[PDB]
Image: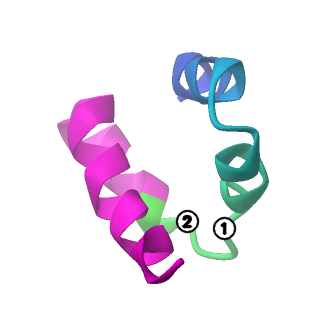
Amino acid sequence: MAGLLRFLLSKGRALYNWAKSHVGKVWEWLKSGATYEQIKEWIENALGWR
């Protein structure tokens, strides 16, 4: 989880701010066992409105 935050921090500053989710369930999936690419796509969808 810590590695994911740093990777995201390197690129996508706006995303970093959005990373501050009020729900732990979103990050729970990572713990269960998933890659950053898969997690990012799901999250990116929420910002797809932009």
Decide if residue 34 is on the left or right side of residue 8: left
* Element type at mark 1: loop
- Whether residue 35 sits left or right of residue 47 in the image: it is left
Relative vertical location of residue 46 with respect to residue 11 in this rendering, above or below: below
For the residue carrying disc 1, how many other residues have a C-alpha within 10 Å: few (<14), some (14-19), or many (20+)? few
Q: Residue at x 40, y 61 (%)?
A: 43
Quadrant of residue 50 within the rendered picture: bottom right
Q: Nearer the viewer, residue 26 or 16?
A: 16
Is residue 36 on the magenta stretch?
yes
Question: Residue drawn at (75%, 39%), measured in percent from left and top?
Answer: 13
Which residue occupies the extreme front position in the image? 50
Residue 8 placement: quadrant: top right
- Asked if residue 46 lies in the magenta stretch, the reply is yes
Q: Amino acid at mark 2?
A: Gly
Which residue is painted at 28% across and 52% down in the image? 41
Whole-percent x and y of residue 12? 64, 37
Residue highlighted by disc 2: 24
Q: Are marks 2 and 1 in contact (CB under 8 Å)?
A: yes
Q: Main secondary structure of the magenta part?
A: helix
Q: CA distance from mark 2 to mark 1?
A: 7 Å
Across and down, in percent, residue 32 comes to 24, 44
Residue at image point 26% right, 34% down: 37
Which disc number belongs to residue 21?
Answer: 1
Q: Amino acid at mark 1?
A: Ser
Q: Which mark is residue 7?
A: none
Where residue 40 sits: x, y (%)?
A: 36, 46
**Side of 7 relative to 20 (left or right):** left
Which span is picked out in magenta?
A: 27-50
Q: Is residue 49 above or below residue 30?
A: below
